Amino acid sequence: NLSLSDLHRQVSRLVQQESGDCTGKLRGNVAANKETTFQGLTIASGARESEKVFAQTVLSHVANVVLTQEDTAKLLQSTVKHNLNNYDLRSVGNGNSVLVSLRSDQMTLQDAKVLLEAALRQES
């Protein structure tokens, strides 16, 4: 996905082009941000729209996904390493949590890896 407004713009554009009866196809490419660093920014404070889409996309994929204490631990290191808490975790188990929301519109690729793997774990 992408931002609601751009998604609607891309879709309206295709409909205007007379492909309304056609089914939509969506594919995107993850890119690493080598321009700016992770600083817990929001759109209002400098986060790129694509950064917010990335972060929110990962967030969506881990909705209700159980995070073990090992997962939580890894995120915690990043939190320490960046001296900033980017997650709203809800205690659901002695050592398990659930991510309910983010604290910024940025997410490091390393953190996304941990989270997406928890999602795949629960899946399998």
Image: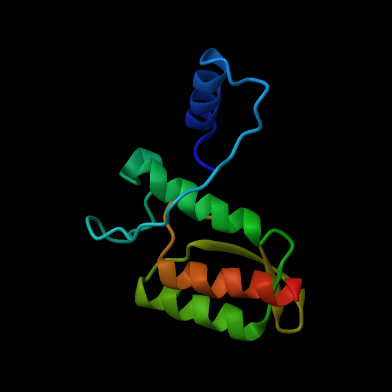
Q: Residue furthest left?
A: 35
Task: Indicate the quadrant where residue 115 lies.
Answer: bottom right
Question: Which residue is found at the position 59% from the left and 78% from the top?
Answer: 72
Q: Viewed as shown, does residue 85 lie left or right of 40?
A: right
Residue 107 seen anywhere in this rendered image of the structure: yes
Q: Viewed as shown, does residue 38 lie left or right of 100?
A: left
Viewer-proximal residue among 98 and 112: 112
Which percent across, then down, holds residue 111?
48, 70
Q: Quadrant of the image for the N terminus?
A: top right
| Above or below, comparing residue 116 to residue 45 in the picture | below
Which percent across, then down, holds residue 117?
60, 74
Question: Which residue is found at the position 27% from the left and 60% from the top?
Answer: 37
Task: Indicate the quadrant where residue 34 lies.
Answer: bottom left
| Above or below, comparing residue 13 to residue 91 in the picture | above
Question: Which residue is found at the position 35% from the left and 46% from the top?
Answer: 47
Residue 42 seen anywhere in this rendered image of the structure: no
Which percent across, then down, holds residue 106?
42, 55
Question: Which residue is found at the position 36% from the left and 57% from the top?
Answer: 31
